[PDB]
Image: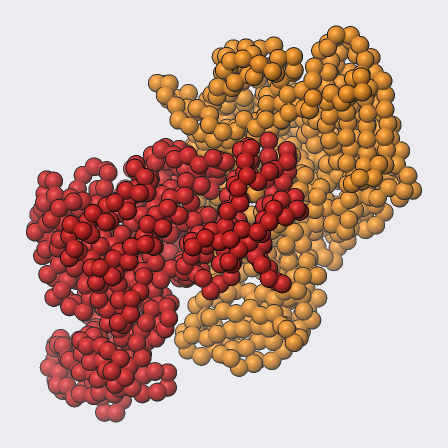
Chain colours: A orange, B red
Amino acid sequence: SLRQDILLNNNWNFRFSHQVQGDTRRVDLPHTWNAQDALAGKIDYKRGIGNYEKALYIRPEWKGKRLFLRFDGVNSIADVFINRKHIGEHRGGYGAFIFEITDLVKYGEKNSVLVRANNGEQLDIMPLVGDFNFYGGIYRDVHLLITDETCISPLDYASPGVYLVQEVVSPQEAKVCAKVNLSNRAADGTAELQVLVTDGTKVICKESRNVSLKQGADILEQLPLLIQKPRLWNGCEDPFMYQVSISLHKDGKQIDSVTQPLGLRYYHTDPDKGFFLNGKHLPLHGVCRHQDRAEVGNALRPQHHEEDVALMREMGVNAIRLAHYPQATYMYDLMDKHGIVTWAEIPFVGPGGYADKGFVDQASFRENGKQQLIELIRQHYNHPSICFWGLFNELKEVGDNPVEYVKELNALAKQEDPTRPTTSASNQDGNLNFITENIAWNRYDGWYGSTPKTLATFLDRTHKKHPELRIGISEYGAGASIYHQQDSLKQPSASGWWHPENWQTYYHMENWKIIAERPFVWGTFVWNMFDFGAAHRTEGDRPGINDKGLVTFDRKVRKDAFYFYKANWNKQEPMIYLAEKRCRLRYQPEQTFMAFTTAPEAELFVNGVSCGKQKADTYSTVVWKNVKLTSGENIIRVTTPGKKPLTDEVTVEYK
Amino acid sequence: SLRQDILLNNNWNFRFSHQVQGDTRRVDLPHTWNAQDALAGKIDYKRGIGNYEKALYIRPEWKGKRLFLRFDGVNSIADVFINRKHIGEHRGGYGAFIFEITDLVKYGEKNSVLVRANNGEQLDIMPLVGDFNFYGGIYRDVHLLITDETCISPLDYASPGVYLVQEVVSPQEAKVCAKVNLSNRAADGTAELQVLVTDGTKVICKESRNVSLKQGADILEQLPLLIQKPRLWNGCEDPFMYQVSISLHKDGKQIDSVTQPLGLRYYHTDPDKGFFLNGKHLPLHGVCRHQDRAEVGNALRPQHHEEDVALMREMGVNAIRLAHYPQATYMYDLMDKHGIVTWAEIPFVGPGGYADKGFVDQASFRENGKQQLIELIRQHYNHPSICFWGLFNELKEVGDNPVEYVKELNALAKQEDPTRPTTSASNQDGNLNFITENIAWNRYDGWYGSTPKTLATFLDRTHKKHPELRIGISEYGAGASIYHQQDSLKQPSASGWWHPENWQTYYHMENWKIIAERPFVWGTFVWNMFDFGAAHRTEGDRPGINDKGLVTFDRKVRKDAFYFYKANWNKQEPMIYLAEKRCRLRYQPEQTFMAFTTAPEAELFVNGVSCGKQKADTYSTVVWKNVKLTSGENIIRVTTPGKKPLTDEVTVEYK
Ligand SMILES: O=C(O)[C@H]1CNC[C@@H](O)[C@@H]1O
Ligand SMILES: O=C(O)[C@H]1CNC[C@@H](O)[C@@H]1O
């Protein structure tokens, strides 16, 4: 009677097609075959076909039901076979996809499921280029879905089949259109469709409709909902969601059901005053996050998403840009749950300072880009956290000019979802910046040359020249190795093998001050919350890594800048953090010590003797200058005021 | 006036000799060139020559002083050049070495220091084989040492030049012979040698001697010390050490000085009753630890040693086998500090289940083995934590038979240091087991076949047949991936790609029970405290890794077995830990839950409803059987008794 969702992750037989003999090894999903070679900095890591095969017992009692194989993600092309007969293809590495196998299997026996995954280079599947790894394989879950022959359809771009369209939302009332896809393979007849909105045990809406479904029908039903005096999803202040059950009934029996969240809110972006959520100004304190991790590549487990979100909330993050592609359903779920305003985007990624192009002007590429956009929007439609749809990152006009195609994507986004604005992330001047509703730039003033001050100049000049633009900062950052430490502050070469941590700290303190004074900037996103994989990189403390994270690739170590942001953004958790603790060897005659704290002041101790109190500045920073160390070991301690104080401590050597 | 010790770790120019053009890149020590390729499971990772060059300013005011380059470790051959002229060679990857450069430099200018490091295969430098990576390069610190022309010699196998020989130790008195190497390059004359033993500010011994030193003299002075009613170094109970200052004086001026610890104790090993420290029985709750780590290979920083020791102490470790080679001075220092009884060993490593040999019977190999043993003993002589010198690991008699050579090494160890017993780690029957004073075996009953019970049978039969042997277990362990989880307990294939965590947990619980009942076993050492690198491995959740750690390779995650040992070994820190939390998906009709706790009992809750209390067994384990889950999410909580209880919690899905 109930819909079943069966995980098919364990024990698949794997081999590369370049291994011609046919023998296989066991693997377990999520899986990528690029977790060792790409992460070792091998620039020509394996990009081609890997094959997964599993024997699936089709239970006799599933006869009469409908059966679907749903894939959460396979990078980048998947060809699926049942009993070695081809059933379909998916092109795109980040969107879910589904095939019905109801009439393709033999009931009561083992059937072969074969997936031939290809992450070889293509010129007709975005992303074509990018500063990250194109990890190959079935790197998200695989499900066997089992439903009634009359069901809420899972066949609409592999979405849940329900779109809760937020037409009008205010504190007085919300009008929602529940769009429901129905799929019928039963004999001609009827069913009753019910849409139930609840808050815990309390019933908020219950709307019903009798529907006549022809054999073979695949149709869209639209049920209007009205909620009086709604409780709004209000970011981290109150991430409230209703639950919606959508169900089908025949003769007073429920025969199918799906649940989706309903987090109601309204928003706008003001060119002069920034982002407003539910009628109130909201600074977007944002970071970016790639979907990979040390040692496992992009084969992330649920605890990895959970941990990433825990670290961001610890830091006081209230906004995120999930670059550079559609990410996991579970990850958008955590954004919903924790109230994090989210920018979600398609992988329409340009070259940046590197070679080749993000756009190749041929129908196959362009049609496939539209498919990946429709996938993004339909598959992730109901997540309240998503407040912006991103259409590109660092495209450029030279050669194949993407401006007209990006206009087509913008119009398609607005058609698919008029309830959210489009955005984009640019490193260019010119017409590419004037298509999406909001615009943002990737700025590295003070890292890739210049000084942080030119970010202030760029922001002010652009805002004055183009007062209609809603200006954001879609990336800003600096590299750091936790193993590169020096007593003095000196700007390093960005592309070199020396990325002292103190420069990243300096960079973020200076850039944050510029942002904090400019409320017309509707959101800013640190590049990046975590170090991440990019095989071609040859910089910092090891190849193959982009080290602009606030936290290391294995999520183990928070860099000093993490705590600068935590003090400023997470003000209600008491803390004190001494900066430059990893710089154990000191040689400067005049030592400077610096702490980040939520307290109004702090006290410094050197070798157990107080150096006195210093006040925190407006950026939660306390600084002591001309501190005198003695030759050899020195114990440095900082303490907040109060009867029960907080402390941080380190032993440094002075010579 | 003072001895100077200057770190030369930053900014060296590096290239491989296979890169013939001559251009270089910046590197910073500690460094290995095998941190990416070997750790990616590349079995033919780079083994050959890497070159490091640094310009060193020789200060005019160093003229008249003596200058030394001291290397803490270079794997495996180092050729050192000053202004591109060869000054010496070291063969051996784990012992320190030193060259005087006093008369080789130009004062008042930059001098070139060039180190040509080679980790290419050799048949004349142990280890010849082994289940670990032979990471190449200058992977420990480099120092410039500056002393008076008359000094406590740093030239005796690069040791501190002072051996505090523990002749007789008891609670009534300790007799120590302070052996001091003196090196003179001043004009013929005299100096006063002082040996000062202190406890904080309190003076315990002060012995002095006037010495006549010819020009060019390199001599040994021996000063007897007598300490009445000493405070003994007593393991974790009281890791007390005196400090010894050894100084040279001319005309009432101190001209040189070195400090060494003096941790006084006595011990013996009883064939029937196990290890006795300072006259009292002491169970050795041991683990093993390799000197590498995720992402950095063996280029460990001080915080890495510190963290490894923190994790071991957290687990209640009181003994360690620092396999399979001499490890860092700083690491033995931490063992001294924290009271951990230590087995230190030379890299005389045999093949185990793999090919080739640990012993090649040729003079060059054998003489070099003796050098590495003398290095080990002289360089690490004064560490109280070291209570055993290990001479080999898994050698075998077939082909080149090492028995007679190992007897030579045993006699050499006893000559170099009669104050500690020799030991060895065997996987063989026969004559190899009857050479060293203590013997131990590497046992994998229940992992590499058989069942844990045959360990009990082996231990009892050996002990009965050979009542004179002091029997230990130098390794025991099982593999586990934290990403391999299954609801049921089933023994996996050791060499396969599936290492469910629950089997490692089962293995350690069963083996520990066998050990705990057998006090004639003087020490046991878990293989291994941490997952570690072994490029040739193809098992568990990724290639290139030996996953028998209780803690993951990046030191981030403690496996369930870590907490079993912590509950049993660290009884005075209150804790409760629910096992199998990583096994999120449950399907067994009858669920079993298991907790490790220091409490006498604990209570289980399922979906907020108590299932009742259960008593902890003698191994700190609480178990609830036939627990009923409901379909879908279940919240599982366990709690200790008391007004302020401890808790552990997890959400599992049942289907
Ligand atoms: O250079 C960087 O670190 C960033 C530049 N903008 C685009 C990002 O993908 C890239 O990673
Ligand atoms: O097989 C194992 O895991 C161990 C067997 N004994 C020797 C170790 O070096 C090795 O790692």
The quadrant holding residue B309 is: bottom left
Can residue B325 be seen at all in this image of the molecule? no
Name the side, left or right, on which B47 lies relative to B503. left
Residue A143 x, y percent position in the rendering: 59, 26
- The quarter of the image holding the N terminus of chain B is bottom left
**Viewer-side residue, A476 vs A430:** A476
Is A41 drawn above or below residue B183 in the view shown? above
B492 sits left or right of A466 in the view: left
| Pick the front one: A205 or A394 | A205
Residue occupying the point 70% across, 32% down? A380
Question: Which image quadrant for residue A105?
Answer: top right
Q: Does residue B413 lie above or below A77 as drawn?
A: below
Residue at point 45%, 48% (across, down): B559
| Residue pictured at 50% horizontal, 15% vertical | A110
**Quarter of the image with the C terminus of chain B in it:** top right
B95, A624: nearer the viewer:
B95
Residue B498 location, x and y as percent? Answer: 41, 34
Q: Is residue B477 left or right of residue A479?
A: left
From the viewer's perspective, is A413 left or right of B615? right
Q: Is residue B599 visible?
A: yes
- Relative to A243, does residue B200 appear above or below in the rendering? below
Tally of numbered tags: 0
Instruction: Tell me where residue B447 appears, x and y as whole percent.
Output: 33, 40
What is the x, y in percent for residue B25? 38, 50
Which residue is rendered at x = 80% and y = 10% of the image?
A189
